Length: 240
Ligand SMILES: *C(=O)c1cc(N)ccc1[C@H](*)C(=O)OCCBr
Ligand SMILES: [Ca+2]
Image 1 (cartoon, rainbow, N blue to C red):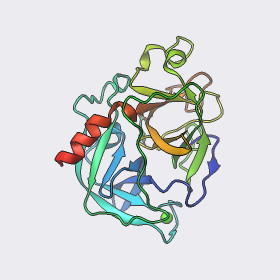
Image 2: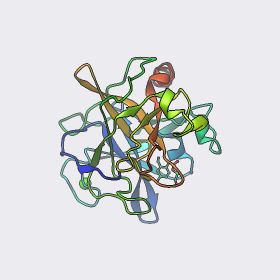
Image 3: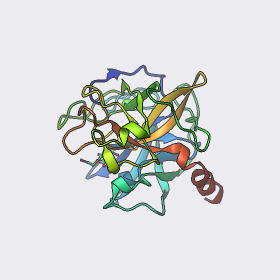
């Protein structure tokens, strides 16, 4: 997260750290959302490589023991059938992971609330992006969970030539574009928490930013619109 603020230890209990075995250690790669006690939702592109993955729940500080962490391995990876590595602008940037075991729910570990199917937020809706991604373009990963206020940009605007143009689709969500705040590398797969009817819900999955940089004016952070995959999500969990 670029231009964000350190998040409170118990503000976003649904946030997870997706890591992969690196030699003799683990390294944060993506964010994700705990949707089930044994299911996590992330970005497809996060699990494109064939590495060993593990999920860290109740995580706050990557390089420090918070006394709240729960480490679980990934048992099964279910990417979206229409997903294609070479075409991120195509969509379908979503994957469901089945955890080896069920995590213990508590103050730091909670299930993310999903939006109802077909739900579209109005322009300039109140949202927050969370993650441990790069704090600066081409910078380094954040040690502690960061957060940034990211109002949404409606399809009509986001799809305009001055913005993302045709690169973006109706099955995506735009947020930010102020040239100051945004998602960055390592934040993707993570949640986009939006306040609807007094309650925060996960309306998107961090997908992509511009090749130019993370924080670029008129280049909002792009997310996979979760409300577009409700049916799919339910079908996967019920069958696996
Ligand atoms: C976000 O999920 C993410 C995280 C990492 N570490 C690498 C890539 C991605 C998504 C993406 O499309 O960015 C390409 C890397 Br310039
Ligand atoms: Ca920790």
